[PDB]
Amino acid sequence: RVLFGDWLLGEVSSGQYEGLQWLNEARTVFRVPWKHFGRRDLDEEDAQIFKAWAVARGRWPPSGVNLPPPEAEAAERRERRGWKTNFRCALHSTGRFILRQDNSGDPVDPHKVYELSRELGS
Ligand code: NA
View 1 (cartoon, rainbow, N blue to C red):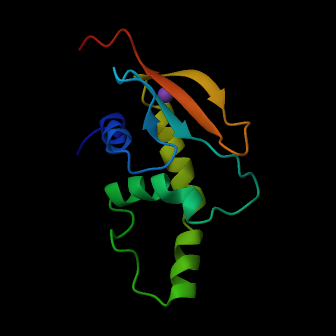
View 2 (tube, rainbow, N blue to C red):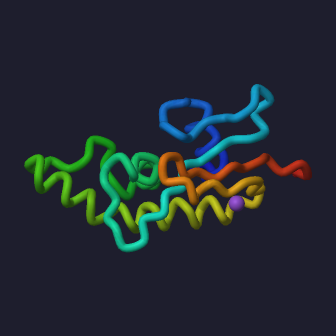
View 3 (cartoon, helix red, strand yellow):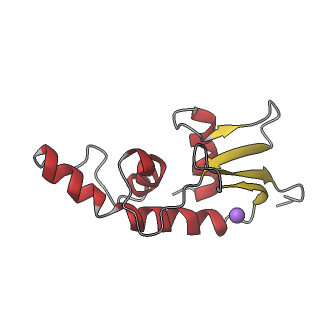
């Protein structure tokens, strides 16, 4: 058990997720991909970070499911909107993260930029 915010910072610093990166050396500001789907389904690429959180919460096996390729995709596909919803709510509930800029409008690279709260005491 770790909090989402600490979990997420570990993923950011990993540099393993495209679009999920630190924006300064000081590591006080980072960006998080933030696509607007609406009606549209999430493909696998759209859901990489959301899926990581679900696996973290034991809501999805780390290896995925042992189904055939088409049925494997569709099984995940049908989970991805809830995963996206669960992640974003968790991020909102992480008061440590202060939204600084909202670039989710840009379709070639929609993301949101957060800063670490300058009043973390204990
Ligand atoms: Na937040």
